[PDB]
Image (spheres, rainbow, N blue to C red):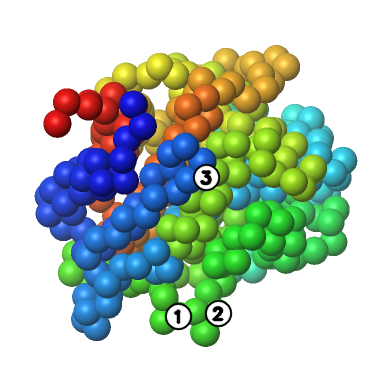
Amino acid sequence: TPVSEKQLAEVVANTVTPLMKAQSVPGMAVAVIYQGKPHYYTFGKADIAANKPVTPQTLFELGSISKTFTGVLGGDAIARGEISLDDPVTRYWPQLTGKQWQGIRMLDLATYTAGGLPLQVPDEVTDNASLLRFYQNWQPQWKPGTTRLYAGASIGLFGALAVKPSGMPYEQAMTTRVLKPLKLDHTWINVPKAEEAHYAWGYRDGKAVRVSPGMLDAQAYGVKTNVQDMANWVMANMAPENVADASLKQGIALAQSRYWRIGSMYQGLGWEMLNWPVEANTVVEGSDSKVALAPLPVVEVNPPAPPVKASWVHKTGSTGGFGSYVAFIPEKQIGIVMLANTSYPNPARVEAAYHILEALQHHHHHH
């Protein structure tokens, strides 16, 4: 039942064309990973005003898909013996002397279980001193390890602390330990002026926009990349047996380990996982912001379960002007990347991606 390029191209087009119309998406780049190989599909415009078409080289903002890079870099640090998820946060930031921090572990930051850290670091925070004030002033609503509340302020901090023992700035640690080893040479925390010709504009309510700088931006939402590098990132995570760098391979395994169970999802490091087989509605309902952003009770997996091959591993991510999603099933060696220059509802992303991967697993051969 080996699905031809043409039949794959038609499946993708048949889902993506109507999606971009219904959601008013100017531009989309799609990769489908199938039998060891990425396949690329591009639609519409990277830049409306200048009439520039999306290509497999166009850069998109990943928004929260950046957190998968943070989890893997953090896993690489663990594999290097530089940090432990079991360590108190104060071990890496002794300045966090507030009593509410006793009992909060690097594990908790990494997996949103610290007790209610907020969705974003406050816009008022502009430097180290104001960042410290923020964490020092923060009053948790729950005790550590009891409630998951998805938060860029939690994993963002985990990412900044993870790299401290390295003595490298985060961008340098990420480039040296993750991006260069995987040959992700068009993946940027800061897009160079030389690369700006490839950088899509984002769109929100008719306005051209790009993500604004912020504290812990690189760790929580600041990665930009094209559909080729993103496909290669998904492949490294889908088939870590192909990752020649040993500590990075082990980091990838740690980022897909199961730390907590929250209903039908398990929380990895940045990555989230549902067991396969999973029905569309279960994945789609999960991505609705009424569930995705809610504080929910966790069940600890003790010790953390190592990666399960029969998983739907995925991550959504947005910025003001961008909406993206990636998913893969390591058992089946298939996966999808959908990068867009408008932030449209997460359940619409998941439904499309799921439809395409389902159509790839249940293709017909009758003509």
For label 2, the crowd category at 10 Å Cα-Cα, with few meaning under 14, some 14 to 19 and many 20 or more, is few
Amino acid type at mark 3: Val
Classify residue 281 by image quadrant.
top left
What is the x, y in percent for residue 173? 74, 60
Classify mark 3: helix, strand or loop: helix
Q: Judge by depth and name the residue closer to the eye, 257 or 9.
A: 9
Per the rendering, the mark at residue 102 is none
Query: Which residue does the numbered mark 2 point to in the structure image?
Result: 192
Instruction: Find the distance from the CA under tag 3 to the CA under tag 2.
Output: 24 Å
Q: Amino acid at mark 1?
A: Glu
| Image quadrant where residue 357 sits | top left
Q: Earlier in the sequence, mark 3 or mark 2?
A: 2
Mark 3 in CB contact with mark 2 (< 8 angstroms):
no
Q: Residue at x 56, y 72 (%)?
A: 190
**Picture coordinates of residue 252 (x, y %)?**
67, 39
Q: Residues within 10 Å of mark 3 (few under 14, many from 20)?
A: many
Are the two marked residues, 2 and 1, in contact with CB atoms closer than 8 angstroms? yes
